[PDB]
Image (cartoon, coloured by chain):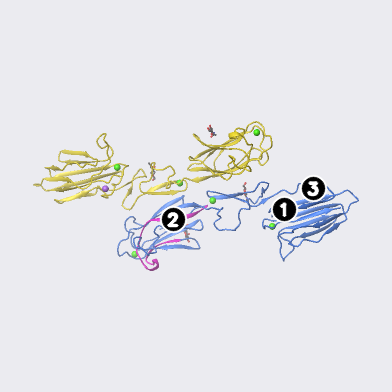
Chain colours: A yellow, B blue
Amino acid sequence: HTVELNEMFGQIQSPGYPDSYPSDSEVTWNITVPEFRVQLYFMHFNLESSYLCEYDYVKVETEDQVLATFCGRETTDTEQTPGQEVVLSPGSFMSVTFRSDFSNEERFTGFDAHYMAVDVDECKEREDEELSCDHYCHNYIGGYYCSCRFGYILHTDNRTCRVECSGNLFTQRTGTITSPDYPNPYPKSSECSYTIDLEEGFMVTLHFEDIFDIEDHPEVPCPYDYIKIKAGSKVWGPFCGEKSPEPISTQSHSIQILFRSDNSGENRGWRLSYRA
Amino acid sequence: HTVELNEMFGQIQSPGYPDSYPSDSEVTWNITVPEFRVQLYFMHFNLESSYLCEYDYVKVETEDQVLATFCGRETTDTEQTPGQEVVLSPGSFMSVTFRSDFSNEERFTGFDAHYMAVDVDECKEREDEELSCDHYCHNYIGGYYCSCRFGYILHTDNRTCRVECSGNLFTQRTGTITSPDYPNPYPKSSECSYTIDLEEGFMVTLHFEDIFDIEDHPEVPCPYDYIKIKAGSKVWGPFCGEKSPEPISTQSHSIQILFRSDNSGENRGWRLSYRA
Ligand SMILES: *[C@@H]1O[C@H](CO)[C@@H](O)[C@H](O)[C@H]1NC(C)=O
Ligand SMILES: *[C@@H]1O[C@H](CO)[C@@H](O)[C@H](O)[C@H]1NC(C)=O
Ligand SMILES: *[C@@H]1O[C@H](CO)[C@@H](O)[C@H](O)[C@H]1NC(C)=O
Ligand SMILES: *[C@@H]1O[C@H](CO)[C@@H](O)[C@H](O)[C@H]1NC(C)=O
Ligand SMILES: [Ca+2]
Ligand SMILES: [Ca+2]
Ligand SMILES: [Ca+2]
Ligand SMILES: [Ca+2]
Ligand SMILES: [Ca+2]
Ligand SMILES: [Ca+2]
Ligand code: NA
Ligand code: NA
């Protein structure tokens, strides 16, 4: 017999329970909960004892993995009997398999068990350091969601937290510009625009101070994050890595700057200055 | 503004949040979950400080009870500010009340909070020693249910555990009869029938030995549990209390016995004997 249901919980007995389970009986149960993990325990366990539970037995098994097997009598110690132990499936699926091989010598009362559903905690994260909340984790029953620190705006991915850097321009002859939340790690999934223009008769110079930190690779030139600068009709970039690019001078009075940062990385960002 | 919704959880901000909450603002929120208790915490708290939070404030209040009040700034210590503390409603209802009295001197950013639902555990029972599981408690998410020990049958009340004593008769001249699971407390909500008949020429005698324990009152004669015996056309009973009734003889060969036990009480029951 193959029986399948869900609810939030359930009750499962051996055939003929509380009385002795019939000979050569083979039964299976598929158990699923949508957002949760399956928890199961045994209120009563009495079965035929054998070597590695070959004859009579109960088997807790997931899709790709077998969780456990149980047989024998709960009264006898040093057994493989489940007793008061509680089996919990990693995934949202659990399958139970009861088998009576051929015949019982002495009649065994069988087993009585009860399952239920348990909320997966994504703040404890279960499986850890996978795709998960950037800043703030919030776990409700049957799922979770994320939020951001004051000043940070939640990105469309519902996971990472971005900021708005596009609202700034620099008028003065001299000054110093940084990355958002410098020296601290720059906000993920963000595009920053820094524009500097001057009245004619002024040539503009640029220098990189302090620490320079951007996620990079010995491979192709800055696939993840980068900085690129536009002066007149000519551009300079992309720039990344630990080593800061050498100081650069620009004839034109008009300069635009782009700093793009991806969804990943803890990289701390940069700082530079400008004078005419 | 009066806003009400449920889901499993939610997010609540002050008016105009993250920016300063407008002057003379008064808002209320009704929050309900069907089977659960309402849990609430604050991710951000910034409000106008005052005496006992008279001016600007947030108020967590149930139907018949006020849970807490909060005001001031989270940055300042020795405050009444909620901070990292978590408010939990005893019942399934929670109401939030935000008020800005008249006007802000300095603009306060307001507050950001998140609620959710939490399973009521009936095995820990919350409020304890109320109507609850006789033998075995099982708590799932959003409710519970009960079961019984091996040999006990669950009564229609879904709570108490009964037994079937009606399937026994006593043929022999001499013998001793007891209550179910004697000396241990008799099963609740049960009706037991013990029948004894003999061939003619025999008169039957009765005596009460050992302990005699039945739930009773100095008031009216055994409203809760009792024993009553039927011999011929005459009856004897009801009998209860600690003191056992005196030995009784019966002319007739036919005797029927009834022992009725209610939903309550731990009383241990009785034992007696019969000889002809
Ligand atoms: C029950 O689970 C088994 C495990 O492999 C699967 O083969 C079978 O199709 C499932 N049946 C139902 C009705 O889900
Ligand atoms: C993000 O959350 C919103 C909720 O408003 C939902 O509509 C959207 O489908 C979600 N997208 C992703 C990629 O999770
Ligand atoms: C909200 O709760 C208050 C508390 O007394 C009650 O008076 C009001 O009727 C409730 N409104 C709704 C829509 O539930
Ligand atoms: C007891 O549980 C059964 C479930 O089969 C339900 O139908 C019935 O209404 C319940 N009665 C009480 C008094 O709880
Ligand atoms: Ca067998
Ligand atoms: Ca969850
Ligand atoms: Ca990065
Ligand atoms: Ca005010
Ligand atoms: Ca519950
Ligand atoms: Ca009683
Ligand atoms: Na930075
Ligand atoms: Na008893």
Camera-near label (2 vs 3) is: 3
Q: CA distance from mark 2 to mark 3?
A: 62 Å
Badge 3 amino acid:
Leu
Q: Is residue B34 left or right of residue A111?
A: left
Residue at the farthest front position: A78
Q: Which residue is mark 3?
A: B169
Task: Find residue A101 and report its horizontal and vertical position in percent.
Answer: 63, 31
Discs 1, 2: same chain: yes
Task: Find residue A175 and report its horizontal and vertical position in percent.
Answer: 17, 51
Image point 50% across, 35% down: which residue? A65
Q: Secondary structure at mark 3?
A: strand
Q: Secondary structure at mark 2?
A: strand
| Image disc number at residue B256 | none
First to last magenta residue range: B35-60
Q: Which residue is mark 1?
A: B182
Task: Find residue A49 and report its horizontal and vertical position in percent.
Answer: 63, 36
Q: Is residue A2 visible?
A: no
Residue at the farthest top position: A102
Q: Is residue B48 above or below residue A154?
A: below
Mark 1 vs ligand 12: CB under 8 Å?
yes
Residue B45 colored in magenta in the image: yes
Along the polypeptide, which appears first: circle 1 or circle 2? 2
Badge 2 amino acid:
Leu
Q: Which residue is mark 2?
A: B40
Q: Secondary structure at mark 1?
A: loop
Badge 1 amino acid:
Tyr
Q: Is residue B53 above or below residue A141?
A: below
Q: CA distance from mark 3 to mark 1?
A: 18 Å
Q: Is residue B24 visible?
A: yes
